Length: 270
Ligand SMILES: NC(=[NH2+])NCCC[C@H](N)C(=O)O
Ligand SMILES: O=S([O-])[O-]
Ligand SMILES: O=S([O-])[O-]
Ligand SMILES: O=S([O-])[O-]
Ligand SMILES: O=S([O-])[O-]
Ligand SMILES: O=S([O-])[O-]
Ligand SMILES: O=S([O-])[O-]
Ligand SMILES: [Zn+2]
Ligand SMILES: [Zn+2]
Ligand SMILES: [Zn+2]
Ligand SMILES: [Zn+2]
Ligand SMILES: [Zn+2]
Ligand SMILES: [Zn+2]
Image (tube, rainbow, N blue to C red; front, side):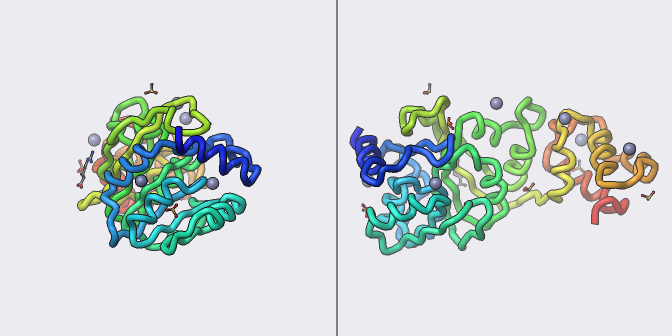
């Protein structure tokens, strides 16, 4: 393992630990890096966003092919290492939490995504304008992203992915491709924005999917009551909601949109 050795050499050169966070797993196989890049069709005109460059193995490959790369890294020591170890003309390193910082404009994402931020990063991405995202997640998370309405793992993530994106698992990635080796496989995921998006009210979606096992009427009565309004105000309106015979985890985007329009009509959503 050429690149695994390079990892050990760099780690010890700067005397740094393999992880700043329990879920840090460096991508250390060149063919997986190149597969991600080729899946994304990275070319000389692309502006790329990466999150968590680590010791910069994917960043390096991106920089050779892309017009510009923005890479977001929380750890200042990692950043110092990237700056000393590489010579790129076309990489802007953004210090901070990728979930919290403002993103530059980009047309593509090519990134390994730490599991700890997989969910908030993906919700943020789905709300941005991009042409294509090729990202690596833990396999179970990727399977959540492509779950179908009514499956056990269909969640708010699944709904928004279906509503806003076209998502494909391109392949599994073995745990052998990272150091340290994770306990589970990863997956390479391709995301493109839907041309005809189903744009859903985020507060409604969160309210419904708080307790996704609940019936649609119960989920709404409970969530709206907890906002601070009397049950008496909303009981009859909620009892006549469309798709009331479903549990929330069975709802298609199209059905959530119906609920939203009904709720706006009845003064429950502003
Ligand atoms: N495994 C893959 N490369 N799948 C490619 C999907 C391409 C995508 N649906 C598009 O509209 O461009
Ligand atoms: O701790 S690693 O398996 O995300
Ligand atoms: O090509 S990278 O090593 O600056
Ligand atoms: O493909 S998993 O079994 O490493
Ligand atoms: O996309 S919103 O539901 O976080
Ligand atoms: O909260 S009021 O509408 O009874
Ligand atoms: O069933 S809803 O799309 O009218
Ligand atoms: Zn980091
Ligand atoms: Zn190469
Ligand atoms: Zn689980
Ligand atoms: Zn619950
Ligand atoms: Zn009460
Ligand atoms: Zn329905």
